[PDB]
Image (cartoon, rainbow, N blue to C red; front, side, top):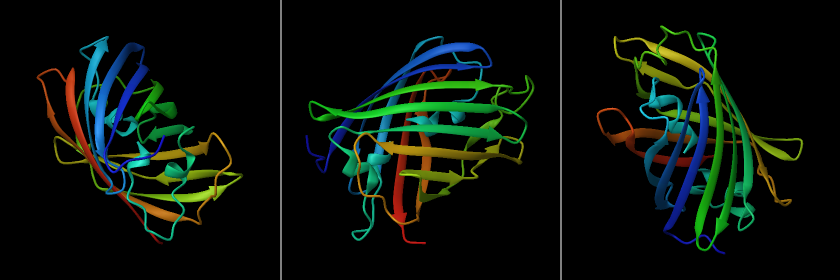
Length: 214
């Protein structure tokens, strides 16, 4: 029931994007105080997916963010009971993805349950045509509001032909018990797909995340 320097996680996602219904199960591990983690994800139902993995990769763990020593770490403080979050991603071409997540600590491992729904992606857009190639480094502003912690970021996906494709992401994180809220601060993240099979039904990803004072 404590957060060790090394921690595994298990994740299950139930998803529908533009009507395509799938599930993913994944196993992760990482170093929660150092801000580093890796996940291996398998599409267990509905593979192969007719859209880019890049809309899914940000949905697979804030207990693994390196926080400065003088900032309350809302995520870590929420355990063992854990926390929930709700996220909306609005992409520039009208696609919307809504995500809700439950995080808990059972038997020495984090357990994540994720529900995702994506709609209104243009059929010939970058998402449904797999035209994207991963996220640029991003800075999530975290700020306290109404007894919850809010995060916001306007991350950019690289396109295969040179462009970028923009999104606005808003997330509300809520501990399951009352915990101390920090003052506003930033989390800097770099999320990479490090390997995948031909049709992206088995995918490994890596993330490094670190909090900084504003």
